[PDB]
Amino acid sequence: TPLVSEEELKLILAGAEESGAIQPQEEEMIHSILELEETPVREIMTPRVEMVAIEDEATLEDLLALYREHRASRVPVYRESVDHIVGVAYAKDLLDYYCEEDLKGRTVASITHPPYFVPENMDAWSLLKELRRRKVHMAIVVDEFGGTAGLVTLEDVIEEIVGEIYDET
Amino acid sequence: LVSEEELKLILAGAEESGAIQPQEEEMIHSILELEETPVREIMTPRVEMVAIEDEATLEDLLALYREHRASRVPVYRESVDHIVGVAYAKDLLDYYCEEDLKGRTVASITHPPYFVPENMDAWSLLKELRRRKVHMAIVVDEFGGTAGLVTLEDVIEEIVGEIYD
Image 1: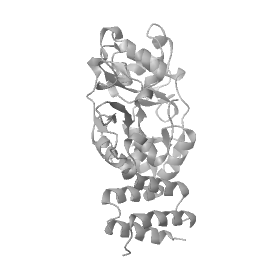
Image 2: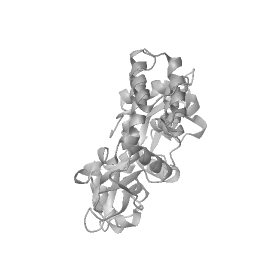
Image 3: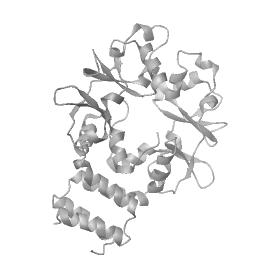
Image 4: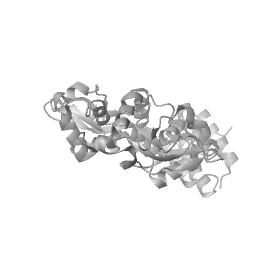
C-alpha cells in the first residue's frame, strides 16, 4: 500500500535494525543487496598488479608449482603479456593428470577455459546475474583502452553480500 | 522504530513503487526467510553423499575424485554414520607422487568436522560457518547418525538462486 522510494527504503531498514525487528547482519546483507547495482566491478576486483597469471605455453608442472607457491585456484592464461588473456586455468584440473602422467608433457593451453570479459564499470548486480548462469565463475576485467584491469569472481560478489567467510585452510 | 509487520509491507510497497525490481526483492525475501529454513531442506542427504574411509590411501582418494568430482569429501571410520572429518581434494597437490600417495592415508589430511542438528536454521548456520571459518557442516540426526551434509554454497544459493555448477 505505501508509496516507498529506494531512498526511503534504506532509511526504514536502518530503523528496523534499531527497532530490533531485524538482526544487524540481516540489515547489512539487505543493504548490500541494494548497493550491488551501484557498485562497479572495479571496486571489488583483484587488480592486474595483484593477480596470479601464467603464460599459455607454460606446462602443467609450472602451473602446479604456481599453485603450491601462491594458492590461486583460478589463474588467467596469457600469450605475450598479461594484457592479452586467452583464457582461465583451474588448479583442480591438475588432479585429472597428477601422478597419471608427466605434468611437463602438457601445456596450460591444453586445459584453458575460454575467457569472459566485462568492463570496469559494469555493476556488481549485473555481474552476479552473468556469472551465475555460466560454467566459469570469474571474469577478466578490461579497462577503457582494451587492457587488462584485473579479475573478479562470483565469490567476490558473494562476499559483498554476506561478508568474508573463509579463504584457504 | 519499525515493526516486523511494517517491514514486510514496506518491501512490498517498494516493489510496487518501482524502488526495487522483483529479483532484488526475491533476494531480500530469501534473506529474511533464512532463519525459517531448516538445514534438512537444503542439505545433501546421506543417501547421496560421496564419502571415503579414513584409512584409505591418498591414492584411493585421488581415484575417488576422478570418478565422482567432489572437491570436499566427508571421511568416516567404520560407516558413513561415524564421520571423523572432511578431506579437501586439492590438498593432494601438496603431496608428492613418489611415496606420499601410497605412504599416507586420508586421515593424514582430514580437517575436523563441524556437526549441526537437522532443525538448525540456515541463518544460524551461516553465522556459525562465518565464525568457525569452515564451508561445510555434517548434519546429524537425533540419534547421532549422519543425516547429510550442508555447505556454504547451499546457503548462498538460497539467497541468489541456483549456481550452474
